[PDB]
Amino acid sequence: WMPAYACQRPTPLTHHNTGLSEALEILAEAAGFEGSEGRLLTFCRAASVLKALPSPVTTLSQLQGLPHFGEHSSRVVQELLEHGVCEEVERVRRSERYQTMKLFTQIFGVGVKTADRWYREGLRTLDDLREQPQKLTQQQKAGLQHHQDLSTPVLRSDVDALQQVVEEAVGQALPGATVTLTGGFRRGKLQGHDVDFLITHPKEGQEAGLLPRVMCRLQDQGLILYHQFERSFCIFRLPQPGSWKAVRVDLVVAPVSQFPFALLGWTGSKLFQRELRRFSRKEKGLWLNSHGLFDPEQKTFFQAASEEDIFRHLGLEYLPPEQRNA
DNA sequence: CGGCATACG
DNA sequence: CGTAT
DNA sequence: GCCG
Ligand SMILES: [Mn+2]
Ligand SMILES: [Mn+2]
Ligand SMILES: [Mn+2]
Ligand SMILES: [Mn+2]
Ligand SMILES: [Mn+2]
Ligand SMILES: [Mn+2]
Ligand code: NA
């Protein structure tokens, strides 16, 4: 029987039920736009279950016994198997609410709450937002100005170039400091919508104060189109053939003692980390975050030298990043 | 029925 | 409120 | 929306 938590099963990047999972993820997204985090989670988990199957679902009976498939998600699959389309999914796709909330929430600096308020105010398009910039944060003005570039997929070739320039700035800010690619690209994705880096130093404590020094140096190189500590959400100026494009880059610093936990957290997927933390607390009674793993009975933190250590601590079989695509 | 991950800027 | 996996 |  397939386990109920996504951290208990390998989930590869590409799989055998793409259309089915994409349909359920539409309904998950729509649930989020309406504030129903519980329904979002169920649809997300049901989608991830299908991503973990070893072959295509061809018949409804193949759902029997799969975790997170009840009446609703089963009916969605049933209709896709019978008619190739699910009326509910298509109604969501076409709805003005879904399209506008998707458009607005995809803006850097705009969340569900902001998008929803704007929708209730009658706003529908990006130019509607541009007409009244007085009500925008600096972060939202940056997200809107750069929205077109930020909607273009980042390519792995872009990533290698960004990593070079980040290492140069890190190397000047603190000799010996290291840069690790995380996020979706570490899980094997060939494209993404941003690039994530994790920075540390092998001498505990030397990483303190590092991120301001890195940012100051990137800014002096003329590479920072926007930025706001240990997490920096930037927009980088990435060279292009005879030009350049804006790219979202996340820079994160962790002391080496916490590096395994921060690597694990920032490598994702988002659902995988939520499931891993849920598993940790509910099944093992341990509290997991990107800083460490806490035993609340003994009041002690687990020491980890690797991701492998963390999986072992939790009684889980190790999963490489490429199998964490829940 | 209560829970649904857990942080930082 | 936003951001991150 | 689903699980325990
Ligand atoms: Mn239903
Ligand atoms: Mn039918
Ligand atoms: Mn990312
Ligand atoms: Mn990111
Ligand atoms: Mn910290
Ligand atoms: Mn309830
Ligand atoms: Na957003």
Image (cartoon, coloured by chain):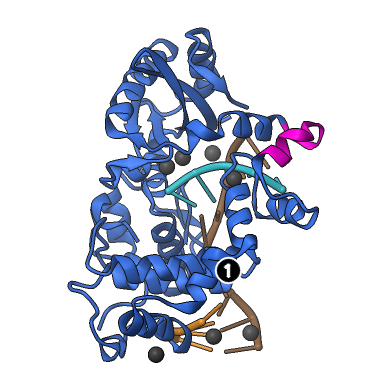
Chain colours: A blue, B brown, C cyan, D orange
| Residue A195 among those drawn in magenta | no
| Residue A128 among those drawn in magenta | yes
Q: In this rendering, would A37 be left or right of A240?
A: right
Can you name the residue that lies furthest to the top here? A220
In this figure, which residue is indicated by the disc labeled 1?
A31
Residue A52: image location, x then y, percent: 26, 69
Residue at 60%, 65% in the rendered image: A95
Can you name the residue that lies furthest to the left here? A55
Residue at 71%, 56% in the rendered image: A116
Q: Is residue A198 above or below residue A77?
A: above
Q: Which quadrant of the figure contains the C terminus of chain A?
A: bottom left
Q: Which quadrant of the figure contains the N terminus of chain A?
A: bottom left
Callout 1 amino acid: Ala
**Numbered range of the magenta stretch:** A127-137
Q: In front: A52, or A142?
A: A142
Residue A286: image location, x then y, percent: 45, 64
**Residue A8 shows in this picture:** no
SS category of the residue bearing label 1? helix
Q: Is residue A183 above or below residue A145?
A: below
Mark 1 Cα within 10 Å, few/some/many (few <14, many 20+)?
A: some
Residue at 39%, 75% in the rendered image: A85
Q: Quadrant of residue C2?
A: top right
Q: Ligand 2 lies in which image quarter?
A: bottom left
| SS assignment for the magenta stretch, majority | helix
